[PDB]
Image (cartoon, rainbow, N blue to C red; front, top):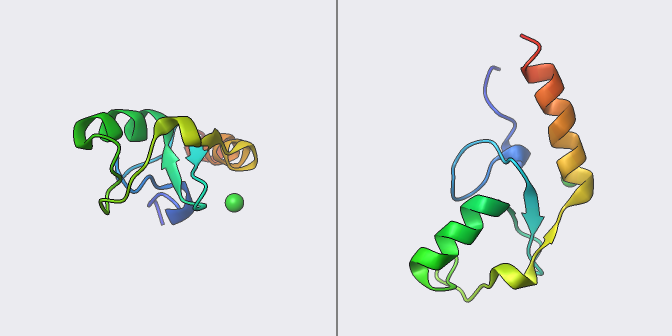
Length: 76
Ligand SMILES: [Cl-]
């Protein structure tokens, strides 16, 4: 599997997450992808529900796991 682990996938950018943010609903996106996407739809997420970039936090644990993935990845 050269493929990116699914938990590190952003539903919007559809690749690797650079910085995980998590919604109150518990959904995980890449920060910059979500920000920009939410501007395009006008605070609606990819299933058309209301969402603001102000109501997300960085997902610290997962950010950390991503850094480790990145170590193993960029090794090859
Ligand atoms: Cl996790």
